Image: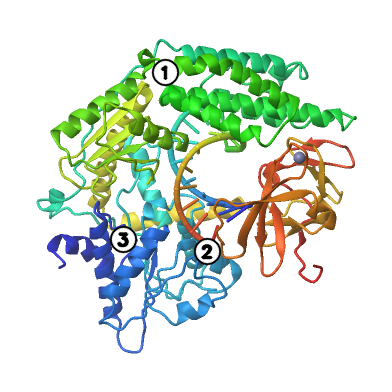
Amino acid sequence: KPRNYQLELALPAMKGKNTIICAPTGCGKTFVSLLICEHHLKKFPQGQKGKVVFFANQIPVYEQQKSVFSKYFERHGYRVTGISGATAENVPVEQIVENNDIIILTPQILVNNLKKGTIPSLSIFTLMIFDECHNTSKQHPYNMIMFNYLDQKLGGSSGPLPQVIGLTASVGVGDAKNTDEALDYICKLCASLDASVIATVKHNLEELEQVVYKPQKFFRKVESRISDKFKYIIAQLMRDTESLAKRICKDLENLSQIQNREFGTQKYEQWIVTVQKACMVFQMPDKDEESRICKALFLYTSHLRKYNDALIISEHARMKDALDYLKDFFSNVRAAGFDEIEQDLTQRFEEKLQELESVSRDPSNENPKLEDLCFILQEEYHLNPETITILFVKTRALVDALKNWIEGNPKLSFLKPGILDHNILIATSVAQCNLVILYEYVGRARGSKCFLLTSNAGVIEKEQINMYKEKMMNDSILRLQTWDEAVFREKILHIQTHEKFIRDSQEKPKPVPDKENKKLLCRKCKALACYTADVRVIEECHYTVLGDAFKECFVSRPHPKPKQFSSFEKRAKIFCARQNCSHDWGIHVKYKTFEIPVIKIESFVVEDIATGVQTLYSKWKDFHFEKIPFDPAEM
RNA sequence: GGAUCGAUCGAUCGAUCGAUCC
Ligand SMILES: [Zn+2]
């Protein structure tokens, strides 16, 4: 039943103006959107038909919205449907939009349609409902739809424009420090979404917080370990590896010029990636020993990166977990390669393992952060044995490490694995949620706690300034609601005019393609893969090769997760067809009836025939050449 | 495969991590 609370948010939208309706409850926002849809479709006279559209960004929320809209809008006789990645194949989306009223298509589908030519004008709709509209920041599908909307509006051909009624939970601040910058950011959001009112409950505050978030904070700053024998042994191993890596590259310290680097930090991983991407462009004229040098440097650098990841895991998670990670990596790479370099590194790690295993089993080397984590878990469960806790972790390499720790720790047995009956649900990013534990990470059950565990004061200061930013965002929302409509509409119109101007400004023309027939080579092998004259672009995003000689240059491998995406269907991945390379080149797909190995320029190095410079690109867009379109008439 | 977002880190750009969509 619609209560007065759900109507105090819908009143500013039923009048016929664009809003930024915001509520902390999901069910509340859904019911408000349903009431707005009902009041908007029922207000039209006879002869006209409404085409309200809903924008869900995720598949689960899309399914929930489609289900609730189909169950609600039944007695009214409105055709409600939905379009996603599993429905926009060989269906005339124009026929779906023209013959429906409450379509709930995802925003990427509407962006693709507006780009293709289907649905030329955006005036076909009469009410747009953006779900979680605080994502309208930059280049987002919501922002691209709003760019088309503002271009058709300010362009001087404004037709029957639709209402752009939004829906969010937090208006968001971004990186504002003073109240002026937060007000500017909220005005920029309201301009990009083109709304004149920010609906927020200012009358019904009594029954607001009965069944809402109502969180709490229990910051717990901890210290790191001191008896770091494992870190010392791994640092000695990495120093030996880096020392024996300089036998072929004397200026390895010269290739990456940033600062002093230390083992076990993200800066070391960045230095590793930089020295990898810098030593992969050698131009030795032998082209035979140069391949061995590049492969040896790639192997040493991959081993250093794995050791650095193991150090970070041992710093955050347990020691046995980092040891298991290193053993798993070594066992996985042992079956792929059999060269003397891999043998040397594996035998060195095996020599160190006889002592690393004894060091890991030492009960006096337990992490203190895991210690007081299990302590606070024990005390909170002794306080209440029916608490469904969620433990957020930064890396996905630790969501399973902490699960193994919970399953192995004898001091606690009441917990169950809940990697995302299941008591604790160890997740990474997003129900009851009776307890949250942000472990090194930077809405119900009134009485729930939220413990933040970290070994750095940085996260504590960031959470403090985040609470201050939430307070200042509430104050700025009150200040904006205090304003009238005229000056606010003029301000948002000026903001969107300036944004349209600066957007028309940054228009990069077509870069002049090189008429030279440059070629591609593997990363860790430097073997001739294919000439760029043999590369065909499929849909301005995907690239493939049609050469018969290229068909034998790779080897297929079953994909761990195949899923078709509106154009193709995945079948397998492709690897380099050498003795001990096994380098990830791309993915094998089917377009309509053919089998095509679509490659990625990330795992490739470009070599020119004119000069001979070896360039390394990241994405296809940065790579400029004669993009020959895919011709099905050939093969 | 491609795009998008967020966090961290490093010289307006780049790297890593995580998530989303097509
Ligand atoms: Zn290769």
Report whether mark 3 lies on the same chain as mark 1: yes
Q: Which residue is mark 3?
A: A19
Q: Residue at x 26, y 26 (%)?
A: A411
> In the image, is A130 to the left or to the right of A594?
left
Image coords of residue A242 (percent x, y)? 66, 17
Label 2, residues with CA under 10 Å away: few <14, some 14-19, many ≥20: some
**Frontmost residue, A538 versus A148:** A538
Q: Amino acid at mark 3?
A: Thr
Q: Amino acid at mark 1?
A: Arg
A28 with respect to A579 (left or right): left
- Between A283 and A578, the one lying in front of the other is A578
**Which amino acid type corresponds to the residue marked 2 in the rendered image?**
Val
Q: Residues within 10 Å of mark 1 (few under 14, many from 20)?
A: few
- The disc, 2 or 1, on the residue closer to the chain's N-terminal end is 2
Label 2 belongs to which residue? A111
Badge 3: chain ID:
A
Tag 3 near tag 2, CB within 8 Å = no
Q: Which residue is mark 1?
A: A361
Q: Which residue is depicted at the point 74% across and 17% down?
A: A251
Q: Reply above or below: A304 against A143.
A: above
Residue A389 in picture, x, y percent from top left:
26, 40
The answer to whether residue A273 is visible is yes
Residue occupying the far bottom of the picture: A47
C-alpha distance separating marks 3 and 2: 22 Å
